[PDB]
Length: 133
Ligand SMILES: Cc1cc(S(=O)(=O)Nc2ccsc2C(N)=O)c(Cl)cc1Cl
Image (cartoon, rainbow, N blue to C red; front, side):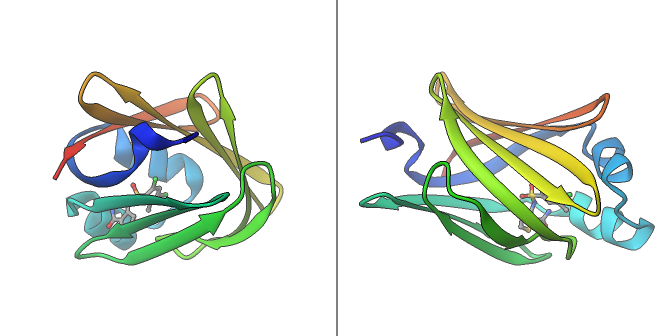
């Protein structure tokens, strides 16, 4: 029941500072432009210990399945090949991605009727807000 409040289908409703976050990550111009336009759906489900997060957009479709605390390989929407570990910290899903000696952290939390996603790369944060579809 660890992630019950995350389960469901979510639609992006607002974004702040995502272009700057993507720049800090190293995303190139054309990908930033096309990824920045998208309004992805995020579909979260749980089966036993396995959590699945799928993102459906006009830009890319991504999917990760994972067990908390257990490192996995991820191909990001911008085509980075990263090593990811996701844990629960005080009710927040904390997702760390490592690649090329770099690191970024994505936090997902429930706040009121929203699912709030905070992406941090060094000093730069982006906030992406989702509501139930
Ligand atoms: C490039 C990028 C995308 C995402 S994303 O919010 O998950 N957005 C997403 C997921 C599938 S398609 C799609 C999109 N914008 O088209 C994140 Cl968190 C971090 C980075 Cl660097």
